[PDB]
Image (cartoon, rainbow, N blue to C red; front, side):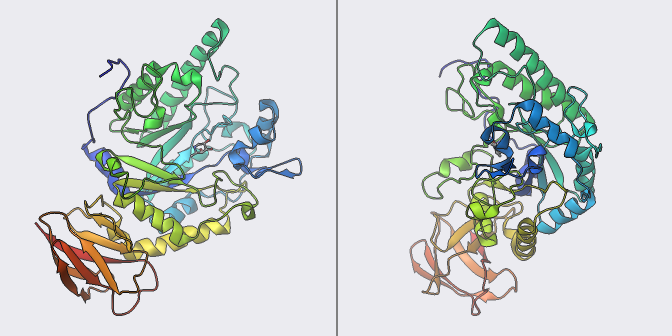
Length: 437
Ligand SMILES: C[C@@H]1NC[C@@H](O)[C@H](O)[C@@H]1O
């Protein structure tokens, strides 16, 4: 191996109770809310099709001008209790919130910059109210944090001069100050999800990513820290120069997912995927007709996909300027919530099952060695093929919702045909298998 002072931290999966809760949660929501929600992907009568949270860049607005949006920040319909009820109803077990996105505007009243929720007509600590409200519903809260900060004059994209070095060094101190602040103001935080860490400035300072991770783990017992934060001695990100995962879990699956046949490597480490509802919109964009919008079944497929391969899935929402959610998102959360009420036993606290992928859908494995078949593609043959691993036998199949026995017929060695239900469920459904070893 190449030796490294700032390479991979521990060996494999954490199995302390905090990581087990992070894992067993499985389904979370993402909240991208910032000044970008005001223009909503439109600058001066020109609608941009790019991601709305990147409008400063699309429309080339200077920092000074972009941040004046603060003067319009007055989410009059915001009600954190309602945000939390909505999440509880969706069956989301955790919410990851943009504390500060690339624009640099903070959703908590930071004492280290003026660009925060304090210096707005609304004044209030949005982050704090959300933390309290989600926690009151027994929902964990995670903090998204963009290292790249377009509002701080000391940020640099690359270290070209002594000047740059003096500035960036001060920037990392600034960054540290905000991180300790979030950690000490909101100690129930369970995770820092770092973003905007890909610039050469950060790659050349791998030492600081390890320090960031280490400092937060001391400030917050059991906190989880994502791989995206981390660079090693040689500038390699996520995985270190010897191929070891840095941070507590892998977080590169953004609007994509690992192949359920070819990428089974992911089962060896914790990981978390995040997804948008449209093609590429994280912040609120006012014109969702500009790209394909995923239906509820398409999002549900991706949730179960992730869990079947040992991962979490986080569904993103981009709240409106006014503090409400658009009706597309409300319909999504309600549709997901209804499905999770019926079928969530096959999601919460589940994991990779070790069975070869089949066309009808996905397997998941429960805490007590239950094996769930989650069927998305209904075979006309009316037979669901199950190939067991060597030594596993199938005792029984039960329709989860009704308890009805489902016929299991042996077809060859380590292979069965599990019948479809007598009555078509009319939606993705679960058959729960009792397996013996
Ligand atoms: C989750 C995504 N991470 C990349 C960032 O540039 C996007 O705006 C989103 O925050």
